[PDB]
Image (cartoon, rainbow, N blue to C red):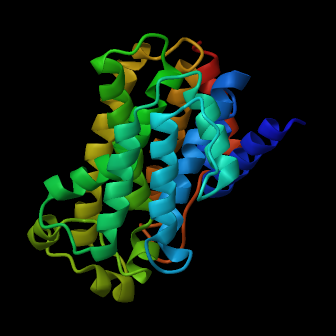
Amino acid sequence: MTMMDMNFKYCHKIMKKHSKSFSYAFDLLPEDQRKAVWAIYAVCRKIDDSIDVYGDIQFLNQIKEDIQSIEKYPYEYHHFQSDRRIMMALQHVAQHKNIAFQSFYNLIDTVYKDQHFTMFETDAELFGYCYGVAGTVGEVLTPILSDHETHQTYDVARRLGESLQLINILRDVGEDFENERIYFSKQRLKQYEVDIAEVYQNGVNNHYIDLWEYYAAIAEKDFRDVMDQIKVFSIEAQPIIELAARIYIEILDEVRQANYTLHERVFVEKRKKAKLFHEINSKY
């Protein structure tokens, strides 16, 4: 194990700890590609989690300065201020692949703003947030998952990232509420006559189910549109992205099977993930 291997193994640890679903799928990529995904995913996770280190923006400002250093001087040695293992790995990736730095900055800007979170007035604001925290991740991963990127490649990766984030929102309604966050928009909540605190206390009801399904239908349609355009990705990445996506679509059914509970985090069994891989791998 070289020092750089240690850095990437740490990024893998971070990715697998945060999401068994994505790790299950992306770890199937060829070695050089999966390591780049681990590094990009790990940087985005550190950014997403940064405010709670001390309780303010210090660490986030350091992550940003580190990324700016890599962008400006990819081939110079930097004494990183945030997490050296992750930044050394990101820099290693940047030395070999085009990295969309402004997408990392859009993500950082979204996380800074989330400090002053106020509910979204409309679905456009919710979808803007999905872009900021997840469509940006799809954008940064685009060159790793495709041989020749076009605006189309980025558009499909961005839409996949945003769809996955909407599924995350649909799975986490209860845990997010506990953490003083409601992502459904005020407009849609008013329209469907739903109060999340009231549902967290009293259980599901038809108004809530209708609202949840309204968003689930949007995620499912976007998923279909991404699958229809899967050929923008490299031949090796195609079944991996289809698997990652199918596992997430499956979380929606797990929520329905659990009667839309706001009191536990549902999940797709590892054994079920393997079943989905078999079904897709047989098509390829």
Q: Is residue 216 above or below residue 97?
A: below
Question: Is residue 250 in sight in this rendering?
Answer: no
Q: Which residue corresponds to the image point at 55% horizontal and 58% vertical from the top-left?
A: 46
Quarter of the image for residue 282 reads: top right
- Nearest to the observer: residue 86 or residue 170: 86
Left or right of 253? Residue 102 is: left
Q: Is residue 136 above or below residue 121?
A: above
- Nearest to the observer: residue 83 or residue 185: 83
Q: Is residue 138 above or below residue 18?
A: above
Left or right of 190? Residue 4 is: right
Whole-percent x, y for residue 128 in the image: 22, 51
Q: On the rendered image, what quadrant is the N terminus found in?
A: top right
Whole-percent x, y for residue 196 in the image: 29, 79
- Nearest to the observer: residue 114 or residue 229: 114
Question: Is residue 134 in sight in this rendering?
Answer: yes
Whole-percent x, y for residue 63 in the image: 51, 56
Q: Which residue corresponds to the image point at 51% horizontal and 27% vertical from the top-left?
A: 242
- Nearest to the observer: residue 160 or residue 86: 86
Q: Which residue corresponds to the image point at 52% horizontal and 66% vertical from the top-left?
A: 59
Q: On the rendered image, what quadrant is the C terminus found in?
A: top right
Q: How many marks?
A: 0
